[PDB]
């Protein structure tokens, strides 16, 4: 199923996700729906809290052929280093982009779709995406890193997008 | 979560649902998402196959205040009698309505959200909704009861609607 | 403010009202205008749909000293028994009256003007008034209970009345 993606300024985007207790068939359905939603909306990452499911589940695909599914359940950041920034987008802040300070290199531990633990070292685009998605799970958005004026301009542009999408 | 509702002429609307093996937390999550979707779309009934979940699950609320949740899992029709018809709508055939022949009274057995069996005798609006929703589960739409030329009128109306609502 | 009361054969009288989401200051202004309208026209009950406001709000005051106000928001009928009938009037059917079958005794649950829930058992005139007003909210009029010939006659009476009303 394709789930509805929340937009700012929805306050559900600010909730802190709980850890997944057990990777069972219910969790695997959520993971599969989240991929289906992410590809439908043409994103490269999606966190459960964006679809109003407040558990620590992220899906990512940064591949050119869109055939490289990465699942992070209960991710934990072990190490990071360096600093970078790319103009980031977000399905919850549609059509807006802004440079945000990130670590350049990241090492994480997570469970996969089978609930098996794995470690992953990432740099480049992948490292940035993982950090962006992990921020969601604690209720943080990329606009939070920006000045109060930039934050206001972004909120306003999104509220205008959505007015028109809703046209009676 | 709010799920996407399929529209004609999607072929997945014609699939025959499988019975629910076990009413567990996964099924209860589906039921809760289905209610959330139905209220969001302002419908009075929704079948699982309309949100691309091909299991025998129906949610209904025909109440005035929208606070009377009825769940039918693995419904079976035990008895029916009489004949009626109102102008029926459907979230999968947006904004179209047509009078369809139905039984006036219906007696069904089903499992509730806890997986407990129950029997229900219905007439009036409820009886009509139950039959409409049970039709979905075997891949049948209300337009199937109409002449080829009304079916063609309805399919065109809906396609115009969707096309001319789809800006990127 | 005094609102305009719709007359038959206005089709807005046949719309089904939505439940009130939240009893806030806007809803409380509507309630106050509805009372002001009802007293102005000298009625004993008024439903929101009669003034082209399609939410589940009803005001009733049978008192002589216009000082026993009753507000029903999102009413629900819990129990009914018996059968009665008096010659009912309606501000939407100017100057016409007809005996209509009603339940004699009625038990309802509703929200008051503050949005606090309450239960009310009624008989006599109040019970009939409550049923009459609850009908308005699902688009029913008292003339709907009468023969086709009686209905046509009432429609004509009212149209003749409003025809004279407007003069130029
Ligand atoms: Ni994001
Ligand atoms: Ni339907
Ligand atoms: Ni009336």
Image (cartoon, coloured by chain):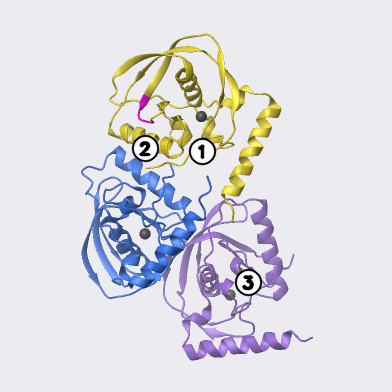
Chain colours: A yellow, B blue, C purple
Magenta stretch: give its range: A66-71
Q: CA distance from mark 2 to mark 3?
A: 57 Å
Report the residue at 53% width, 89% height from top: C152
Percent x, y of residue A49: 46, 32
Crowd class of label 1 (few under 14; some 14 to 19; many from 20; radius 10 Å):
some
Q: Of circles 1 and 3, which is in front?
A: 1
Q: Is most of the magenta stretch helix, strand or loop?
A: loop
Label 2 marks which chain's residue?
A
Residue B166 placed where, x, y %?
50, 50
Numbered disc 3: secondary structure:
loop
SS state under label 2: helix
Name the residue beneath numbered marker 3: C62
Residue C141 or residue C108, whichever sits in front: C141
What is the number of the mark on residue A33?
Answer: 2
Residue C124 is labelled as none
The answer as to whether the residues below labels 2 and 3 share one chain is: no
Is the Cβ of the residue at disc 1 closer than 8 Å to that at disc 3? Answer: no
Q: Which mark is residue A6?
A: 1
Instruction: Please rate how many residues cluster around mark 3, counting C-alpha atoms within 10 Å: few if below 14, some from 14 to 19, many from 20.
Output: some
Cα distance between the residues tagged 2 and 1: 15 Å
Q: Of the residues under marks 2 and 1, which one precedes in the sequence?
A: 1
Q: Quick check: can you spot residue B100? A: no
Evaluate if marks 2 and 1 touch, with contact meaning CB atoms under 8 Å apart.
no
User: Who's the residue at 33% across and 71% down the image?
Assistant: B148
Quarter of the image containing the C terminus of chain A?
bottom right
Is residue C26 shown above or below A131? below
In the figure, B74 relative to A38: above or below?
below
- For the N terminus of chain A, the quadrant is top left
Q: Are marks 2 and 1 on the same chain?
A: yes
Residues flagged by tags 1 and 3 on a common chain: no
Give the letter of the chain under mark 3. Answer: C
At x 55%, y 14%, the residue is: A84
């Amino acid at each position: 199923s394709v789930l509805q993606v929340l937009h700012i300024p929805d306050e559900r985007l600010r909730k802190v996700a709980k850890p997944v207790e057990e990777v069972n068939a219910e969790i695997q359905r959520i993971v599969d729906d989240m991929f289906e939603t992410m590809y439908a909306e043409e994103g490269i990452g999606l966190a459960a809290t964006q679809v109003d499911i407040h558990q620590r589940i992220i899906v990512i695909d940064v591949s050119e052929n869109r055939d490289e599914r990465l699942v992070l359940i209960n991710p934990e950041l072990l190490e990071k280093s360096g600093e970078t920034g790319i103009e980031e987008g977000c399905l919850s802040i549609p059509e807006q982009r802004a440079l945000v300070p990130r670590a350049e290199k990241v090492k994480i531990r997570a469970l996969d779709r089978d609930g098996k633990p794995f470690e992953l070292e990432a740099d480049g685009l992948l490292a940035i995406c993982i950090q962006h998605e992990m921020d969601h799970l604690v209720g943080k958005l990329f606009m939070d890193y920006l000045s109060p004026l930039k934050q206001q301009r972004i909120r306003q542009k999104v509220e205008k997008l959505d007015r028109l999408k809703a046209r009676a």
